[PDB]
Amino acid sequence: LRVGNRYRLGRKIGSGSFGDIYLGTDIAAGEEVAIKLECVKTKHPQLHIESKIYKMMQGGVGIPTIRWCGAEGDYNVMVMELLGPSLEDLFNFCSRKFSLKTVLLLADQMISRIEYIHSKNFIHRDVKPDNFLMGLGKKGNLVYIIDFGLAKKYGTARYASINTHLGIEQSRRDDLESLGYVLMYFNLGSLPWQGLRISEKKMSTPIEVLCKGYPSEFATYLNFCRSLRFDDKPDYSYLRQLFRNLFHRQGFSYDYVFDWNML
Ligand SMILES: Cn1cc(-c2ccnc3c2OCCNC3)c(-c2ccc(F)cc2)n1
Image (cartoon, rainbow, N blue to C red; front, side, top):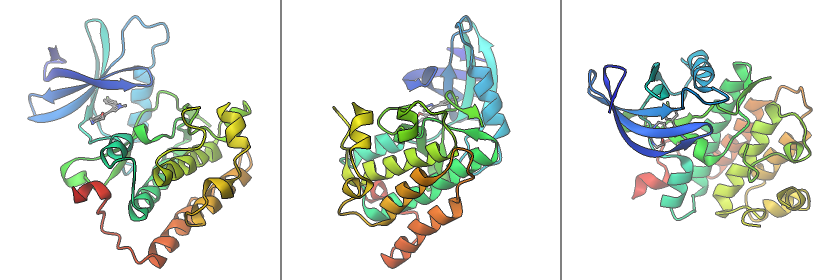
């Protein structure tokens, strides 16, 4: 179907936090795009709020470009550049196993994405594999952060921080602690509180038991995040340096060759 004079709406590929995702084509520029549809009459409209967040975050590395914003028939329409698969899709495609090199290359970029969002006075609140996409073509080495539907100016139970389970207001430390669980999830293939209550299991699982058999940096990362105060500005540089020093000790080259590039 025709959308905003130049876009052609394609098939539904999935969903966001508050709307359906579709594939699409920018007919004028000759480029494939991603289209997010809301519902004009929705009780809690949020698509234009999210567009404002994306607009404010433009210019930042790994922040997707929003091409158009409007309303077509029954829906509010946001048009974004086409990005690649999610880290969740890539993990499943890689048989739910990532090499240490891949986990570290992902960690370096993911910490930077979270830090940029925080530098722009926002917390993400839903740091999970599904919310990170690899770019396509020339941007195939780039980790993009998506979905600002749950974002707030300063989530998923599997990756939620202990503070979140306790019902505490989310802050900068919570986005980073969630990233720590995502990194361990990539190392193990699953988390001990997956497919189980989750709060009880997370609190009864010492960081050292969770990270057993894996480099100490993953535990040090989670311990640092769990030690941060509510209003604390996290030391993002320290956390990246933690994984960067391990990357160098392992003798890996920062060449952006991920496990999926080997298929
Ligand atoms: C959950 N989700 C995922 C994509 C997504 C974005 C870009 N490209 C793709 C996306 O889906 C993954 C698969 N690759 C194709 C969005 C999205 C967001 C805003 C928008 F306006 C449009 C889409 N949301």
